[PDB]
Amino acid sequence: DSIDTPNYDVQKHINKLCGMLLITEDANHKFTGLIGMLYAMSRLGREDTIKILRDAGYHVKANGVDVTTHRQDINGKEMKFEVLTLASLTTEIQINIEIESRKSYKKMLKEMGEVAPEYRHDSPDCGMIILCIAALVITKLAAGDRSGLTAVIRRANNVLKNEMKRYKGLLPKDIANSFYEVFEKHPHFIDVFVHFGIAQSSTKGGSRVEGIFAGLFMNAYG
Ligand SMILES: N[C@@H](Cc1ccccc1)C(=O)O
Image (cartoon, rainbow, N blue to C red; front, side, top):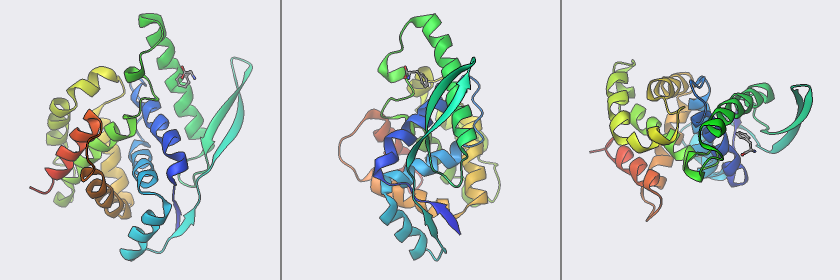
């Protein structure tokens, strides 16, 4: 029925939401599967996402995704939070993700001073790092269970070694579980993910993380 169809205009915001989870020490990855799927949809854009969903036979009521402001007190001081209009993810859950991310960011500040771009929550490759785990999970979905979980974790520790040094919240077990859950609960995300992975993998050049993603995705075929 009602599905969030993020467009290109919110892609940066979703990438930062992925980044916020990636910098959180012992992050609660309950919504990471859904957030990574929202990121993949924002890369495809609303028109292509709806086309994929309808072509696959799904009944879709598209919910447009805008950025909005919510006010909330922190230490008795009013803070302004930018959130997305998502039918699948409440304002409260999004704000809690940011609050927990800010606590981990303060610990990083105390240890190393201001944080370098590649260790920040707004690094351009944050959404793609999350989708690297999804590429691994998609290879083990046919089993009808989570038996492939151990192999997912082993491959992620090897292939994503550099990204794990950058991010304390890059916990392959928890992120892989969140994707297994998102794909079991909402199988239409499998179609979306596969179309994303194909379109992503054919792109020329790009970042180191884009190359890692293309390698993992293509390894789910050969
Ligand atoms: N806006 C600040 C503080 C912040 C840290 C982590 C998450 C959200 C906000 C920064 O990006 O440096």
